[PDB]
Amino acid sequence: DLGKKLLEAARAGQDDEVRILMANGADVNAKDRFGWTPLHLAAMEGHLEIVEVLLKTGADVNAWADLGTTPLHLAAMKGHLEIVEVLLKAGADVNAEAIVGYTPLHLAAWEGHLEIVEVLLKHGADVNAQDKFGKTPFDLAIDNGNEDIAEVLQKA
Amino acid sequence: DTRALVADFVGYKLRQKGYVCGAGPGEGPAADPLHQAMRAAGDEFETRFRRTFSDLAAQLHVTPGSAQQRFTQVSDELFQGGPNWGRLVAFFVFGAALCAESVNKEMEVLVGQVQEWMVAYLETRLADWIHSSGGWAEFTALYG
Image (tube, chains in turn blue, yellow):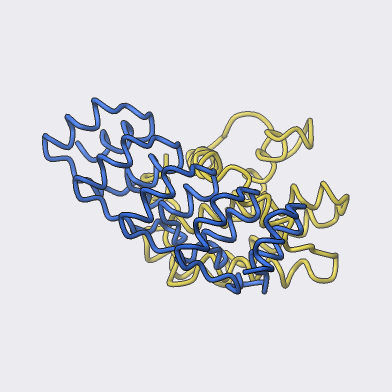
């Protein structure tokens, strides 16, 4: 059950344990009962070193969980800027859709992370993307009172 | 069966979040493996997504008139590309989140009605899938 152990170590941010498991043949793409991989867990918990090791060892940067959630959605939502950059460099899909048709730009805009919104924009994020209910990132930014982000999205 | 599961999970989450106290479904520890399984699964699912489903619930801006349609739209979205056990857990987490949001906006009738709509959705939509997938006994095996 190396896969289960890799999932646990990735979430807990145990760098040494992750390298040993990988060197012992753990499946870098193992999925838990919600469809999350080690990359999803490390991205959400903000462990940058583990994200980089997983990618170097073949982790699927675009893997999606049960609702379509990708590691970039989680990094964007939680506001981990360095992980967002690393994921984008590795081929992360800026336009992936999850849950209700949320795009990583929707999640960064709602959570008020301005620099991440800008990075996503520079990498091709669709400013006009609508979730299932018609809302764009601009709409979510404003509704959560993030004016700074709203203005940036309007200009874009 | 289904009604009891919904009542237990929603009751448990409302108590967990401090919205309600005292006698009723969801009060005290799970009486039943199915109920324990859904509590544990909902809890784990929710710690991952943090405020995601509470934020979605709020984004709907439900009114007593629109709430059923909005609930139904979200549920349909969650089940896009077919049901699996994880999407079912999301559906319970969202239902409980919508009940909590209704408490926030002081629509108390919706706390009960959303639970009614959850049962009806399960029975009329996901019933066929659940049964063929091994029923709730299988869910319990995997998530308990």
